[PDB]
Amino acid sequence: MKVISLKKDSFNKGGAVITLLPEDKEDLFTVYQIVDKDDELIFKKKFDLVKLKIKVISEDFDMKDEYLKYKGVTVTDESGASNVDIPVGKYLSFTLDYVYPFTIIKQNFNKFMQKLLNEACNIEYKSDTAAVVLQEGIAHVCLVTSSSTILKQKIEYDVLKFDEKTEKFYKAIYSAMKKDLNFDKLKTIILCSPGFYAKILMDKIFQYAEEEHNKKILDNKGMFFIAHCSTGYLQGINEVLKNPLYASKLQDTKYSKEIMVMDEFLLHLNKDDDKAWYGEKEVVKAAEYGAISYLLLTDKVLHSDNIAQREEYLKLMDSVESNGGKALVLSTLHSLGEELDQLTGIACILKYPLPDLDED
Image 1 (tube, rainbow, N blue to C red):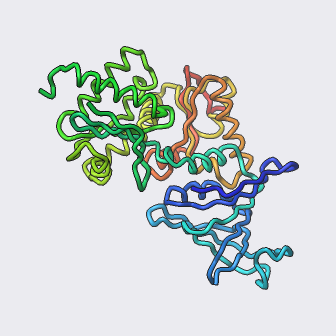
Image 2: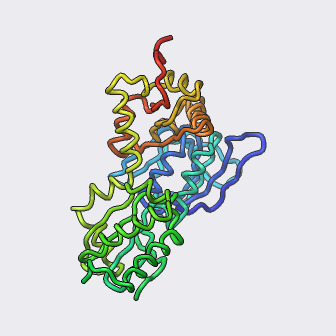
Image 3: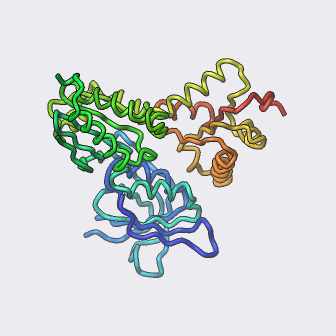
């Protein structure tokens, strides 16, 4: 994502004018979480490219197809900056492309949407993925984009045997990781190699973490994924990424924390624990007692038509976290989010049982 400019208001806290350029399919999903019914879009269409402007009435979104089309009606522009000689009220659609920026004009831009919009501009963390590709005597610490990979540091210098040389290797590779990698932003870390190196590196990183009591790693073994590839050079990473035997596992690391929380949530729910609830009413109540350890929301529910509800939900996240809980957003592009959606899109795990939250 590229943001060209972004102007907010004085008198209207939700007001913004955003000019941006989506660059890949993930950007299409970001955009989708921002544009609301009744926002206006100014865009270029070739049907010579002219500037047109519509008020959004509905949309057509399909992740599979890299497809996002906004449908609305032309509005008047006495500016002459767009919709020149085109009549007010005309039906018009805008299918996003990766070539020309367009402009969103919104009244209800919120702090959550801005985060999303920003995270989508961060070019090396957009996909939350690092990798270390190893061979003997050479390891590359990397960040992975959806098109490239970024060499972030190079390290160089029977295989299962202890050596003074190889010990300084791994210890180096591991320090070049906590130095070059924001473990607080990453959800996947591929360790891959020919032979045993990736696995040895994995074991080492974990020795070292236990030693330093480094808890940002230890508390997150879920993000690590060891894989095989032919060589210790950058091409290896792409082998892993393109390899179908690693597809499900690649996803399971990225949603590792979500898999846990959902497991834990279903655990309580399937056990009449009173420590798990779903429904706006139940969760709103729960929050009132400061009892929520996990707040669960779908991304769908946070950019709904219901601005009151979506702001309630947004505060609810501030509330729960300020009270010592965690809040997470479940991708509705995947089964966990789909699942939560079936339970109204909002749910919670409580710190301690609370009965009759559904009773009035």
